[PDB]
Image (cartoon, rainbow, N blue to C red; front, side):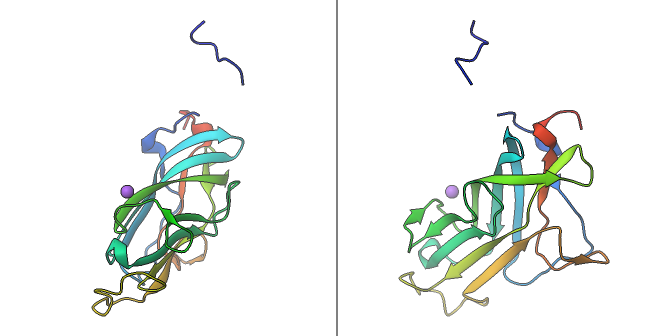
Length: 176
Ligand code: NA
């Protein structure tokens, strides 16, 4: 009885979530960052829910105008906001380190035991449009910039992106 559902996901082995490509060099513009997927769950067909982890050198939360994922290939929208003064979304405590859930479309990876998500960007905007300007004049970097995530735009082992996208087993299976 207890094992039968009442009507009409699989989490991926964490060790099997890893980068979908490697390179000798990656783009090094903007503050240093560490951006990766840390878990995946199969929803249905080519749709998964993933945990994106972000760490980067930053200003303070009060300086932050907007922080969002853009260009996302997803059934629930091309944009996910993590912080937006203008749209009133307040989902993180610290801009330097946070996770977020993303629902994403996938495609078959080179090794077809795995699937991978599509390229996307993380746009960061500081010190404008109602954000505090305190400490913004000591900031060495631009006030607005984008981390580019992808396994595309790679020539002879050099990527023009900041970080790879991630792959994980198809259906979050344990076969791989
Ligand atoms: Na948080």
